[PDB]
Amino acid sequence: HWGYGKHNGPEHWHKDFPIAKGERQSPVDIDTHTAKYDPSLKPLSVSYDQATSLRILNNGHAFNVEFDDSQDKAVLKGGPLDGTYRLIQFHFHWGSLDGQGSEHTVDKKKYAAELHLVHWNTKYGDFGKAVQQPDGLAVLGIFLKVGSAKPGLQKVVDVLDSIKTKGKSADFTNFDPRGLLPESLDYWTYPGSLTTPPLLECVTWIVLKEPISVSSEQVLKFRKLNFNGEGEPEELMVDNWRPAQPLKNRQIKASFK
Ligand SMILES: NS(=O)(=O)[C@@H]1O[C@H](CO)[C@H](O[C@H]2O[C@H](CO)[C@H](O)[C@H](O)[C@H]2O)[C@H](O)[C@H]1O
Ligand SMILES: [Zn+2]
């Protein structure tokens, strides 16, 4: 099936997933000088106080930290969003080197990695139903650059030896995602899609202006992960990011001047 190499990567996806060339695909380049400040965007509201993490999983494309979304525990509201979006999982996209790895770009700048915190609109009852709606998902995108360590990431970095290969997972309870946020909640927002197949155009993207810093030793451990399953030839999990796609008939709004 699909992945990130020469033969199965982002240039091939359209063959099985023709929406890949669609109206509202992600990621995109964020041109800071074309984005329109919108004084009527409400403040963004991140409520991760009661967040219940369960498990970390290597799915052969990335690793997912999954949350209990059986009630309104950790939710995203405000900003450009209507109603409540429940957190289900976060994951990253990262590079083989520090100059690449993020999906969105800022004035063409690629960051070392990009965090995605994935939320579904509760008005739709479950995740499977929400992916089928234009306002079904809200994903909070946060850029990572390399510098000093993010202490709130270290617990994630430590568990990765135990989920090296596709299909492995470990228990991952009592992890707090507020430790992955920057100080500022300033953001750009546009309507878009999942950046992995099935590339469903159901996402309101909220991309934070301010990056988090991670140590070099922290990203190096991401890069020690494996695309392959146990006992297969080693393909390092690196460069699992889709490049930027045409903006087309869309506007990126900024929460800030
Ligand atoms: N990069 S992304 O956030 O657009 C992309 O979207 C999917 C999530 O909506 C995908 O999901 C993984 O976890 C979800 C949520 O439960 C699904 O169940 C799916 O089967 C699983 O792959 C990607 O992980 C993510 O890259
Ligand atoms: Zn993602």
Image: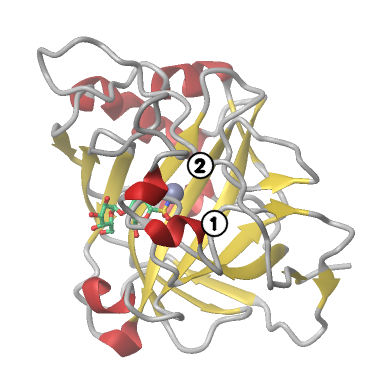
Position in image of residue 22 (x %, y %): 51, 64
Quadrant of res 215: top right
Q: Nearer the viewer, residue 32 or 255?
A: 32
Q: Nearer the viewer, residue 103 or 21?
A: 21
The answer to whether mark 2 is within 8 Å of ligand 1 is: yes
Instruction: Read off the residue under disc 2.
Output: 242
First in sequence: mark 2 vs mark 1:
1
Residue at 41% in and 34% down: 9
Residue 17 located left or right of residue 141: left
Amino acid, disc 2: Arg
Q: Which mark is residue 26?
A: 1
Position in image of residue 164 (x %, y %): 23, 22
The answer to whether mark 1 is within 8 Å of ligand 1 is: yes
Residue at 34% in and 32% down: 8
How far apart, in angstroms, are the residues tagged by discs 2 and 1? Answer: 8 Å
Amino acid, disc 1: Ser
